[PDB]
Image: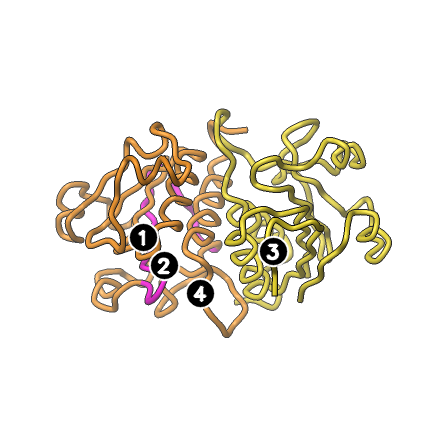
Chain colours: A yellow, B orange
Amino acid sequence: MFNVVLVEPEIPPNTGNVIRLCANTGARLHLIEPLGFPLDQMRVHRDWDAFVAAEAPDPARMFAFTTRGSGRFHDRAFEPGDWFVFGAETRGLAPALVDRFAPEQRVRLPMRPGNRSLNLSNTVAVVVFEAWRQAGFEGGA
Amino acid sequence: MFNVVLVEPEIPPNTGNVIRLCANTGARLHLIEPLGFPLDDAKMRRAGLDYHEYAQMRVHRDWDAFVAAEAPDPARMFAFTTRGSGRFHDRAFEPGDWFVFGAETRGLAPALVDRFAPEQRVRLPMRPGNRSLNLSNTVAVVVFEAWRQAGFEGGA
């Protein structure tokens, strides 16, 4: 229903949590190597162009989570099979990658200004659930 | 703004995540003993928690002690359970509301769920199966939704 994409994730437990969140919600998981850890509906990609090559996402429906040049995630309408792109919990998305995203495809979660990053799994769960809400919690209940 | 209550949390990391979720959204955190892990300023700091984040949380001895010390409005105190519950997103939430979660392993003890009126019972939508949504993910989805209903008052 939704595609969650993790770019070079670092902390094993986060992905674990994300993997499980996808099962519970019907979302698909994409990983962009390199990963910070060994990992023994999900697909690992070698780097970003390979992912772009293999999945050919609709650029208008692929959203990046960045605090620069973005709007509020909740101000946008989402559709099934949207792509939601998250960076590593520490760095976030490399600027070079962010540079590949149009303003309107730049999103962020409201937060108290401040402040440390939300755990990645939490960030992904809120994102998927909000999109799911808009999609009427189809298939769920 | 909102109140999160974790009743006998078992797994440390989940509580560290919730401590961060709280800091980040402005929610007040309540823990109900017994816990699964020691709670500690140092421990929390090596887990990557600042001192603004965890300073102003409250630990209670048991459910009675909590009810005593806080006196939550019953009509605005919601338990997460799958038995006798409505869908979470089908309700309206107000500043000051209490959201009550059980341990990752079992969820809320039956006995506790028994003190909750049906209209004060809720669940997250989920593919039937299954397993539990992770504790901290569950809490973050709930706070953010309530906060969404509140206009993300004080945020961005």
Give the amino acid at mark 4.
Ser
**Residues flagged by tags 4 and 1 on a common chain:** yes
Query: Which chain is indicated by disc 4?
Result: B
Q: Which residues are magenta?
A: B90-107
Q: Residue at x 24, y 45 (%)?
A: B73
The residue sitting at the top extreme is A114
- Write down the residue under mark 3: A132
Query: Which chain is indicated by disc 1?
Result: B
- Write down the residue under mark 4: B132
Give the amino acid at mark 3.
Trp
Q: Residue at x 51, y 47 (%)?
A: A122
Give the amino acid at mark 1.
Val
Calculate the distance from the C-alpha at mark 1 to the C-alpha at mark 2.
6 Å
> In the rendered view, does B36 fall on the left or right side of A72?
left
Q: Residues within 10 Å of mark 2 (few under 14, many from 20)?
A: many
- Residue B99 appearing in the image: yes
The residue sitting at the front extreme is A38
